[PDB]
Amino acid sequence: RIVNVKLSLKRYEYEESRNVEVEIVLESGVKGYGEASPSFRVNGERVEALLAIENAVREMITGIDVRNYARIFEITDRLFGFPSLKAAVQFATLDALSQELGTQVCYLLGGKRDEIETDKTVGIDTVENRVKEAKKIFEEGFRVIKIKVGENLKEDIEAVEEIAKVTRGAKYIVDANMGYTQKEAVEFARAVYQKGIDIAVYEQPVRREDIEGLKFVRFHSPFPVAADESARTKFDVMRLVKEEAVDYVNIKLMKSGISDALAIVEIAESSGLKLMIGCMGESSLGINQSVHFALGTGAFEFHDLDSHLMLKEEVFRGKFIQDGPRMRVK
Amino acid sequence: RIVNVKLSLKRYEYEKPSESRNVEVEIVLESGVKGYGEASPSFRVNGERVEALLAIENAVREMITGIDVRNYARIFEITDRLFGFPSLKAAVQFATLDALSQELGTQVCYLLGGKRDEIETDKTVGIDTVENRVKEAKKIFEEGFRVIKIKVGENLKEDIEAVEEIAKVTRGAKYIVDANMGYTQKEAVEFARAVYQKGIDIAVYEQPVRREDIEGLKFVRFHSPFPVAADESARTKFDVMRLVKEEAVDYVNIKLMKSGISDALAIVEIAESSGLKLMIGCMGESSLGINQSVHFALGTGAFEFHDLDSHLMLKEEVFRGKFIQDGPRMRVK
Amino acid sequence: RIVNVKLSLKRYEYEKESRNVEVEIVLESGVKGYGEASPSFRVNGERVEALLAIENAVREMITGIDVRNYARIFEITDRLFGFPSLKAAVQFATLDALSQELGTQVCYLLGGKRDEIETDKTVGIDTVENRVKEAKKIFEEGFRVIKIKVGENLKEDIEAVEEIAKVTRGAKYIVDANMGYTQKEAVEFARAVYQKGIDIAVYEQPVRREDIEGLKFVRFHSPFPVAADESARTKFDVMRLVKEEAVDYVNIKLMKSGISDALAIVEIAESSGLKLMIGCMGESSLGINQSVHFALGTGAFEFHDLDSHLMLKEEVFRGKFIQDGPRMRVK
Amino acid sequence: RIVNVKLSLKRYEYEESRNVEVEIVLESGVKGYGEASPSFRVNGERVEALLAIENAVREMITGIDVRNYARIFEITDRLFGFPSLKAAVQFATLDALSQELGTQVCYLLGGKRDEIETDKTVGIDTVENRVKEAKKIFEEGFRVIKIKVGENLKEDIEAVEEIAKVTRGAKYIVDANMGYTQKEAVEFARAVYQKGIDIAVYEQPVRREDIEGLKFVRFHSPFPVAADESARTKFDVMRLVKEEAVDYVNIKLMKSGISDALAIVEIAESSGLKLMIGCMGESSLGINQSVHFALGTGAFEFHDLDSHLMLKEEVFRGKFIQDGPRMRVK
Amino acid sequence: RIVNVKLSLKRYEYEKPFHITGSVSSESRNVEVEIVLESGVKGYGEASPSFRVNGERVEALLAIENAVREMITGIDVRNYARIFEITDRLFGFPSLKAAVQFATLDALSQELGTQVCYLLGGKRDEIETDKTVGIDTVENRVKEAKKIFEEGFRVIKIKVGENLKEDIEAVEEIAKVTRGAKYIVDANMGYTQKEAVEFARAVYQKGIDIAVYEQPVRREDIEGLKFVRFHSPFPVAADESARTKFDVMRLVKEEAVDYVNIKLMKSGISDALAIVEIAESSGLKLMIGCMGESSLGINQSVHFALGTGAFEFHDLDSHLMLVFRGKFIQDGPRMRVK
Amino acid sequence: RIVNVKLSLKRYEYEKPESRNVEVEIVLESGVKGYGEASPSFRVNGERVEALLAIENAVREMITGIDVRNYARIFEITDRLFGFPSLKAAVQFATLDALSQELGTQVCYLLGGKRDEIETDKTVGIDTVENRVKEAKKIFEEGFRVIKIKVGENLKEDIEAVEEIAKVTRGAKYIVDANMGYTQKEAVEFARAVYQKGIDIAVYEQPVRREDIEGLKFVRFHSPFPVAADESARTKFDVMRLVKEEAVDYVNIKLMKSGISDALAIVEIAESSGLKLMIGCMGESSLGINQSVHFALGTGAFEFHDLDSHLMLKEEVFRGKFIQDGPRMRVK
Ligand SMILES: [Mg+2]
Ligand SMILES: [Mg+2]
Ligand SMILES: [Mg+2]
Ligand SMILES: [Mg+2]
Ligand SMILES: [Mg+2]
Ligand SMILES: [Mg+2]
C-alpha cells in the first residue's frame, strides 16, 4: 500500500525544461518514480498548476495497494486535465509494483523486445544550421531523423531535400506540428515525393480538431500520415479509427497516461493502425517511462524519445541502458 | 524459461443432459514452477474438435519451448497463430500467466490489475419443458443466485412463456437471455417486445440472430428495449472493432475460449473506449478452467455480468481452481 | 449411399515437402470418389495432424447419405469451417462419385462452360538473379501468364518485377504481395511498376486480411485491378467485400471455401461486377483436379493459378484431366 | 446436342391462362419440356410476342450439347425481355439433361428435400367471399394461406382478421401487390398485429421501384417483408441486399429464369435473406419447374406454387407427386 | 380521337456493316407506326428496336399490334398524357412505346396547326449532329474519320471497347486528321473499370480532349461508372445504364455520371421528358442518341432536341448511315425547323 | 410575338380574418391577350407586392419580341426572376394562356389534358376550438370532403381542435398544415396524439422550420401519416435535395413558389422517385387560381388539391377560365 506521494519541481537546462517528478512510497519501503513533463500547447497544462494539486493527488491514491493498480489507474484517469501528472503517477505505481514483484516494468508490460531505436530531432532553424545538425546526428549513429517543419512550406520543402542529401541511408519522420492547411500539407508531401525522398511518417500536418483534414491528407499523401495532437485519449483514437483518418497515431505518455496508452495500443493493433511513440521534455528518469513502455509492449514501428538527449544531467537517472541511438534493459 | 509443455484429455460428467471433454495444458519452467490452463473447445462456435486439439501437442510444444515467461508477450504473439484452435490459445496463454505470476510471487488477477476482489456469476436454466424450466429456476434462485441465464431460441411462443413463468418464481433476480442465434430479426424483436409488455426486464439479450448477421444485431438493438449482446459474432478483437464501427451492439460477451487472453485484453480496451458494456461467459470449463476467467474478471474488473457456471454443472471430487467459490460469489484468497 | 469415407496422409516432394490429406468416398454401388485437402496453417489456421485426427467424425457426418442428395452432404460439411481444406476435399469427392454414377464428369455437372483453361506458373521470392532465371525457364516452357510473389522488400520487389518483365515480353503478370505491404507501400508498388510501363493483370492481397479499408484504398489508387485472397475465404467474406466495394477481384481457393462457398462466390461475383481468378495451396495432381473441373465447369475465371502439382514430384499423374503445357482440358 | 426446339401456345381454363410450352429434342431422342407463363404487368411480356420469336430461340441454342448447359444459360440470359421463355428453355434444357444422366432435375440441383408444402391463394373479393375461400382452403388441408390485398386498406385489414378466425392453426402470407403507400403499408401491418394476428411473409406492399419504401416498411413492420416485383434479376437482389431493404425475396422462375434464380439463392444464403418461391399462371407441367427447383435447392421457407391448382387439366403433366398441399418426387 | 393504329415492317440497309463492341449490323428493320384520327389527320412514328440494349426483337413488336390498338383507340390526342401513361406499360417494347407516343404528338400538332418541336417548347431553331466512326482496322477508322471531317462534321463519335491498345491508337490517329473537331468516345460497356480509366489517361496524356466518354463499363456496374467518373479527366456518360427515368434518378442519387445519353428508343417520350427535368435539376448534362432510325424515325428525336433544346451534343446520324421522310431540314451536319 | 407586358395591382377583400395581387397581362401582335396573377408572399418567398410592381419595365424588356410558340425561351429567361417567384409564375402562365389561344385550345390540354376534373379542400384557419368546429361544420355542409386544418401555435389546443373537427365532419379526409410551428419532438407528438384518437391525417404539411430537412426526415420516420414539404420545397433544386435526403412523403407544389418552370420539373422528379404530390396556393383570386387549376388538370399529378384562396375572397364576377362546381373544378 502507498503511504505517501510527493511532487517536486525539477528543472533541466537544454544545450530550460520544467518537469514535476513524482515519488510514491509504499509500506514496504519501496519507492516508485515518475516524471510529468507538461505541455501548455498540447494539454493546456502549466507546471505551477501541476504543483498546486499535490495534496489532492496524495489523497486520491494513498492507502491503495499497488497490486490493485487498476484502481489507481481508474482514479488517476480523473486527472484528465493534468495528463502529464496522470502519466507520472501511473508509471510510478508500476515502477513500485515491479520492484515488489522482483522484476522490471517492461517485463510487467510483456517484455516483447529487448531493444528499441530512437530518432533524434532536427529542429526549426536556417536551412544551414538544420543540415549541419542533421550531419551531426547522422554521425552519432542515428538512422531515423525527425525533421520539424510547418511554418514555411517552400522553405520546409527545401530543408528536407538538403537534409536528405547529407544523410542518405537514414529514414525520415516529418512533424509539421499543425502548421499547414490541408492543401499545403498535401503539396508538402507531393513536392518531397517528386524529389525521390521518402518520409516514413508524416506527423500531424493540420489542426488538432481538423479530423477531416487529416483524412484528406492521408488520402492524397504518398507517405503514412500520423495523428499526434489529435490523439490524446483512447476516445480520440477510436474516433480517428471510426473516421478512417490516419495511418499512424503517435503516442505520448504525457498526453494519454499509461491507462489510455495501453488502450490505444490495443485499438491500433485491432484496426490496422501503426504506432510510434514520442515525448515532451522528459529528463532521463522521465524518458525511462516511455522506454519501458515501448520495450514491454513492443508496439511501435518508430521511437521519438530524444528529449533526455537535449538536456544536461549530472548523472543518468533512467532504469535502462542508453547506447548510441539504441535503448535496452539490463 | 519453458522447458516442457503437456496437453492432456480430461473428461467431466454433467448432472443433466452429458460430458465435457477438455484439454488441460501444463507448462513447466526450468525453475520448476508449473502453470496450468484448460481448453474447452466448441465445434459449433469455434469449429474445433477435441481430438484435433490433442493432435497438435508437438506443434504447441515447439512454438513456445525455450521462451522465458517474463517475455509473455512473445508467447502471446506466437500463440495468436493458433486462431484455428482458440480454446488452446487461451489455455496456453493463461498457463503462461499462471506460471509467471508464481515466479513473481503473486496471482494472475493482480497481474491483470487487481481491480476487484469479488464477482458474482449467474446460473443457467437450459432449454426444457416450461415446467422443468421453472423447476430449475426455483432451485437456482433458492441456491442464492440472483442473476439467472435463460436459454431460448427454439420456440418463440414457448420461450416467451418460459421467461414469464421463470420471472414469477424468482422475483428479485436479474435475467440474461441467450437465444443462441435461433431467431430471425423479426422474431428476436417480437421476443423482446412481448417480454417487455409483460413488465419483465432483461439485463442482457444475447446473440438472437445468426453470427454473420451484423446488420440483424443492429436491427434488433434498435428495436429492443433491452441491451443486445454479441457472443458468436464476437470471437476476435477484429470482430469487435467491426461491431463498434457498425454500432451493432450494446454488449459483447467475451469468452476466453473464443478470444484467448490476448484478444480478450484487446476487447476490454476497445469496449471501454467505445461505450460498450461487457459480460464474460464460458464453454465447458472445469474448475481449473473457470479459474482462468475468474482471475481475468477479477483482475480487469471489466464485466457487468459474469456467466461462469460451467464448473458448477460438472462433477468434480476435488476443486481445482485457484480461487474461492462462495455460493454465487467468487474471490481470491 | 456412402458406405465409407477414408482420410490418409499423402506426402509430396518439391522440385526445389507438401503434406496433404487424401479423401476417398466409397459408395454402396462400388463407386469411389476422391478429393484432396491441402491445409494451410497461415491462411486457414489448419495443421495436417489435426485434419487426420477427425477422420471418424467426418465419416460419421456423412456415411449413409445418398450422393444424389449432395446438397445435404454440402450443408453438413459446411460445419467443418475450421477444417476448410477437408470441407473442400469431402465435397469434391462427393461430386466425383456422383458424376461417375451419372455417367459424366464433374466439370459437366457444374455447367461444362469451357473445354480448356490456362494456368500461370510462379516465380517465388529469391535473389533477382534467381527470380529472372525462374522466369526465363517458365517463359521457355510456354507459360504466358506468370505469377510473381513479392511483399518482403518494396524496393527489391519493384526491381524484381521490372527484371522479370524484361525477359518475358509477351506475358501477362499477376503479383501476389501476400499481405506484406502497408497501404502506402502497396500503392507505391503499383505506381512504380506502372511508371515502368509494366502492366499487372491482377495485384493480389497487398495488405493484411482484416484490412478491408486498406484493400479499398489500394483499389482506388492502384492502376491495376486489386484482388482479395486471404480476405476472401467464405461467401460471407465476399458479400462483405462487395458491400464495401473493396476490390476488383476475388481469388477463389477451394481449400479456403470448399465447393459450397465457392459456388456462392461465383454467383455473388457475376451479380456484382466482381471478376475472379482461382488459386491453390499445395495440391498434387489429384487435388488440383478439383479446381480444374470447377474452373472448366463454371468457366468463371479470367485467370487460373493452378501450378501446385507442377512443383511436386509424382510417380504417376493422378488427375482426371489433361495437362498440356500451361493448358488443361477434359478428355 | 439439341437438334430442335419448338414453342406451342397452350391455353388453360380457370375454375384463362395462356402459356407457351417449350419442347427441346436432343440427337439421342430425349425430349425436354418447359413452360413459359408470361406476365405483362410484371415482366412486360405478351404471349403473342413470345410465340413470334420461336425461330430466334431455336437458332440460339440448336447444336449445343446439354452437358454444356452453362453455355445455353448464358445465351438465354440475353432473353431478359422474355424472362418466362428464358425460364422454360433453361428448365427444358435441365429436364433433357437429367434424363441423359439417368436422374431427375431436383437431384441434379442438389436433392436437398424430399417434400415441400405449397400454400393456396385467397383472392380479392368481398370480405364474405374471402372468408369462404379461406374456409374451403383450410378444409382441403392447406396450412399456409396466401391472402391478396392492396385495394382497400380498411377492408384488407378486416378480411385478414376474419380469415384468421376461421383458419386457426394456419400461417399467413399477405401479398399487397404494390397497392399500398409506405405509410398505408405500415398501418396495415400494425393494425393486423394489434389483433394478435401473425403474418409469416408480407409481400411487396409498395411499388417496384420504391426500394427505400420497402426498407421503410421493413423497419416498421413486425412481420418479415418480401420483395417480389422488385426482385426479378440477380442484380435487383444484389441491390436489395446492399440497401438492406427486405427480409425476404420471393423468387419466381418466370421473372428470373433458372440462371438468375440460382444466383439469387446463393446471394440470399450469403446475406441473411430468407426466400420463398412463387409462380405466375403455370399449368402442371410448368409448376413442375418450380417444384424440382424447390426440392433440389431446398432453399425456401415457403412455397406459393398453386397456379396449377386453379386451372383444369384432364391429364396431370407434372413430373412430381401432388398430395394435398404437399409435393414430392417419385 | 384515335380511330386506328397500324404497324408495318420497313427495312433499311446500311451503307456498310456497322461494328460496335460485341455487335455488327448492316441492316435496320424498323416498325413504323401510323395513327389515324377521326379528323382524318395521320400521325407517324418509328420504332427501331434493340435486342442488346432493350431486349426487344422486331418480330415481337409486330405481333402486338392488336394490344397497342386496344390500349389507345378512342382516346383524343389532346389528352396525350393519358396515352403516355397507358403506353408506359410497354416497358418491354420501349421503341414501340416511343413511336406511338411520338405519333400521338405528330397527329396532335397537326390538329393544332403547329409542329412537335413547338409543342415541346420550341427552344432552339437549330441543332448539330455528330457522325459515327465504327470499329474497324486503325487505317479504316482514320479513313472514315477523314471522310466524315471533310463532309463538315465537327463532332465525331468514335466507337471503341474491343481492344484498349488499338482504341488508344485509333483515337490518336483520328485526332491527327480531324483537328478542330470535338470527340465523343463510346466503349459500349467494353472495358473494366481499370481499363476505362487507363483509356482516358492515355488519351489525355496525348493532349487529346474527349467531350463525352460514353458507357465504358457494364450497364449494371453503377459503382464502376462512378469510379471511372472520379479518375477520368473527361465527362463520363451513361447510355445503356440509363433507359428509364428511374434508372436516371438512381444514377443521380449515386452521383455516378456527368452525362446521360437519352435515346427515345430506350425511354419513349414520357421518360425522356422526365429525364430532361431530372438532369436540369441535378447538374447533369445531356446528349441525345439513336438506334437504327430512318429519316422518319430520326425526325422524332430532332423535334425532341429542338423543342426542349436540352442537349449539349446530338448523336442523330442513323439516317445518314443508311428519299427524305423527316419533317425537318437536313443541312450538312445541321438540322433545322421548317 | 409579345408586344407588351403590363402589371397592375389588384386588391381583393377577404370575408373573414385583404389580398394584394399583381395581375399580368401579356399582349401579342395578333391581338391575343394572355393573363396571369402573382400572389406574393413575404413570409415564404420574401416578396413584397410593391417590389413586384416596381420591376414592370424590366419584365417587359426581358421577353418583348419573343414568340410565345418559343415558350421554353420565355421560361428560361423568366427563371432569372427567382427573387420574384410569384411574378415568374404569372408571366409564365400568361404566356401559355396566350399560346393556347393562338393554338385554339386550353392550357390544361397543352399540359397533357390528363384529367377532366379535380377536387379542392377548404381551409379551417386558426381560431378558438369553438369557431374551429364552427368553420369545419360549415365547410362540410357545403359538400367539401377534404378539409385543411391549420395548426402550429399551440400543440395541446391543436390536438383538441382536430379531434373536435373530426367528430363533426365524419367521412371527410384531413390535411394538417403546422406551418413550421413545431419542434421535431412536438411535431411527432401531434401525429401520435391524433393517431391514438383513431383519426387519420392524409397529409401532414411542413411541421418544422424550412431549413430543417433533417427534422422533416425525423418526423417522417415517426409519423404514421404522410409528411409533406411546403416551405422547404420552393425550387426543383430544393426537391431534388429532399429526394436525395429521403426527407418527405409529399411535396406541396405552389406555382407562386416555383413558377410553371420548376413546377413541371418537380412533377417529373416526384413521379420518378415515389414522391406523392399536392398543389396549394397563396392568396390568388379566381384569375390566379385558374393557373393552378389548368396545371392540375393538365398534369393530373396531384393526390390532393388545396386551391381555395379564391373561395375566401370576394369577387362579384368570376374571372377564371374553368368551371367551379361546388368543391370540384372542371374545364369547358
Ligand atoms: Mg508531434
Ligand atoms: Mg451465448
Ligand atoms: Mg494469394
Ligand atoms: Mg407477389
Ligand atoms: Mg452508346
Ligand atoms: Mg403550407
Image (cartoon, coloured by chain):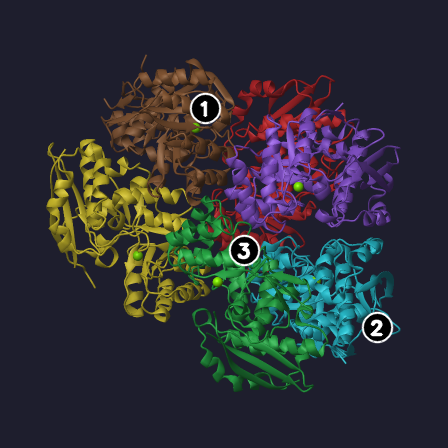
Chain colours: A green, B cyan, C purple, D red, E brown, F yellow
* Disc marking residue B320: 2
Measured Cα–Cα span from mark 1 to mark 2: 79 Å
Residue in the foreground of this view, choosing between D314 and B34: B34
Residue under the point 46% across and 81% down? A49
Measured Cα–Cα span from mark 1 to mark 3: 57 Å
Instruction: Identify the subunit bearing mark 3.
Output: D
Q: Residues within 10 Å of mark 2 (few under 14, many from 20)?
A: few
Measured Cα–Cα span from mark 3 to mark 2: 52 Å
Classify the position of ligand 2 by quadrant: top left, top right, bottom left or bottom right.
bottom right
Indicate whether C319 appears above or below C90: above
Q: To which residue does mark 1 refer?
A: E169
In this rendering, does residue E163 appear at all?
Answer: yes
Q: To which residue does mark 3 refer?
A: D221
In this rendering, does residue C118 appear at all?
Answer: no
Q: Nearer the viewer, mark 1 or mark 3?
A: 1
Q: Residues within 10 Å of mark 3 (few under 14, many from 20)?
A: some
Label 3: state its secondary structure. loop
Instruction: Identify the subunit bearing mark 2.
Output: B
Label 2: state its secondary structure. loop
Q: Nearer the viewer, mark 3 or mark 2?
A: 2
Pick the quarter of the image with the C terminus of chain D: top right
- Name the amino acid, label 1: Glu
- Name the amino acid, label 2: Arg
- Name the amino acid, label 3: Ser
Residue in the foreground of this view, choosing between E207 and D75: E207
